[PDB]
Image (cartoon, rainbow, N blue to C red; front, side, top):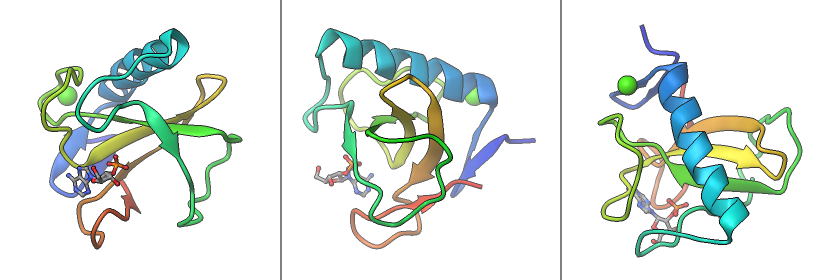
Length: 104
Ligand SMILES: Nc1ncnc2c1ncn2[C@@H]1O[C@H](CO)[C@@H](O)[C@H]1OP(=O)(O)O
Ligand SMILES: [Ca+2]
């Protein structure tokens, strides 16, 4: 069973925790990776009900289980805040353009 389903991708809570840890560390270091410079700020214009406060930041989560290191980020993301609290798992899959929907 998947703790989060993004389209056809299944993630366990460990896969979320591992990607969040990596992304938070780059945030603390003032560093980014990838042509699109992740982690970067996330603005919640779609109004997802995140129960943690912003600012929010997004970091790719990979279906492969590997930590994102540059290269294609795929469509899935972990969102965390300034206090390293998990806000949610969203994806561009099934959303028009560069918009998002939440993973279920
Ligand atoms: N797999 C993907 N599907 C849809 N949008 C993509 C995507 N990969 C990157 N993006 C979006 O492409 C745009 C320009 O790179 C950014 O808004 C970026 O959003 P993100 O960084 O929030 O994912
Ligand atoms: Ca996994």
